Length: 135
Image (cartoon, rainbow, N blue to C red; front, side):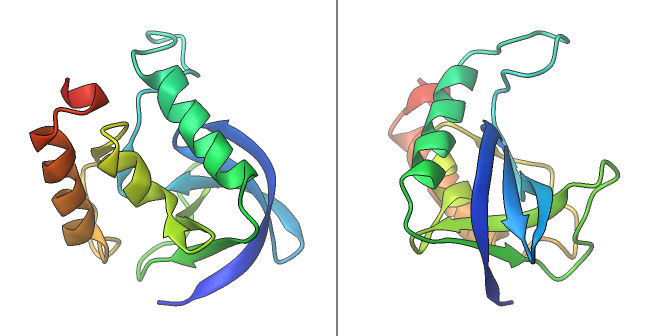
């Protein structure tokens, strides 16, 4: 796997960000994580949704560098979103959300599962520390 440069366009939700990638605007969905959402009238603004969303927003907004890392399998989903690990100054946003108890590890689809172990390890720690979602 390799990281590539991208430029923030707009943070959209805890688990979705819009980036400039290879000169085209594109919506990215964060691989392997489920955050509570703000956007979906199914329930509306779930609990910790505003919080997960504020966290991803600040993280990508205050970064000097954003990089995207595609996994080994398909790189877009049925809605046309890029499927990727997102990095803000070297730190994986997907991991940080999970480390903070602001996201769970999603259902995993091989072969898009390279960082699955790492994330599950952070999730176990957040649970143990009873952070946010695990409170």
